Amino acid sequence: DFTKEKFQLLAISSLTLPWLISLAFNYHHPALTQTLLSGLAVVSASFLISWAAETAEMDVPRSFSLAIVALLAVLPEYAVDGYFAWKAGSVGGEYVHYATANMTGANRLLIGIGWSLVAFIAFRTLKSKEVELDDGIRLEIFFLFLATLYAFTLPLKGHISPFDALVFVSLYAIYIYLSTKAEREEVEVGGVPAYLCSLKTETRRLSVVVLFLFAGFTILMSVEAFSEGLLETARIAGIDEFLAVQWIAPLASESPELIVAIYFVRRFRVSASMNALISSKVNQWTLLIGTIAIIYSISAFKLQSLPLDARQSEEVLLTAAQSLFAVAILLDLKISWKEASALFLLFIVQLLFPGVEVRYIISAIYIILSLPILFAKRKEIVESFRTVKRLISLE
Ligand SMILES: [Ca+2]
Image (cartoon, rainbow, N blue to C red; front, top):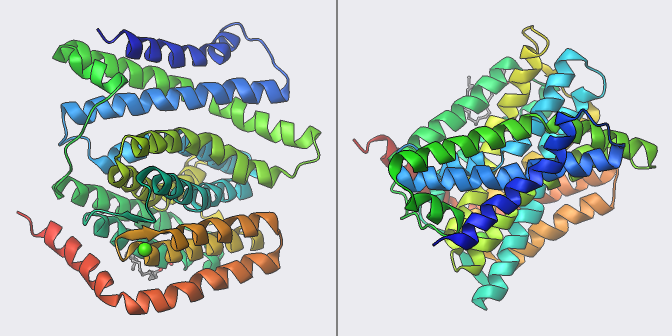
């Protein structure tokens, strides 16, 4: 049958239409409505992409690791942040700061809001006070630690060089490579992917290719209007543009990923749900950084480092600090209510109390909180090192 899921496909696909039709007829909307419509299209195309990636994963598991599907789940973030980086190199000006602000916003929101929210919902759903993670998480923990240690070298220099980007991309490439050699969990299907998997091979694969291309096309035809729409809306209002770039824009990019995470929690799949959020942190804290720095050179057609002013350096430091604390929490392969609430509070406090003083204070707290945990769980760091050591010598 699959009539219900066929209607779910058509319904959300149709959500791209208000913006796509507007593009087709070259109709100009005011700032806010342009943001809503183009944003509606981006979010919609994101679910399509996820539906497409999950079908391909069930189809050919060896080509689509859980890490890769976690990357494809946050494509709108790469496209929006990529747009800022493109403008930064081709035009310059405020877009230089926006590229880093958007990236740090995405990362901190993911942990501060995403990890905490999903954990809290899991608490009420399982009627418990602890979330346990798989042993395979030690992989992402290792790369998270290396990326974070490397990211601490960025506020010092005051920029992100082409070599830095090379490192971050290398870390992710190696991570992906090792994620293929790791024993994945059995991929369940439900909803749209289950209907797509029901179709004969060539029709199934043609369909998700069409979906990928259509959704990918939609995103690329939407991000500029959505990004400029946001910036415009914030300007005619009294709101600082940095708040829109850092907090509002990633919210629209990380929402589809969050919604899918919540869905899997209620279906009693907490482990896989957290695996994706943690792996998504990995790519956004590796590949994303490399991408914006690389794009900064490409759009300018010149070998160039992405500058980091006083503000953005503090943002990166704060983000690295939060990420250190995140790593230390994951070491026991469990997420408790204290740790989740700590992630939430320490995040929103910085957001509700702006200023250079608070950025340094919260940075210090993240780091100082991390050290006793890291010291008490030093065997877990060694274990994470051995996990990677085994994946290398698998064959
Ligand atoms: Ca923990």
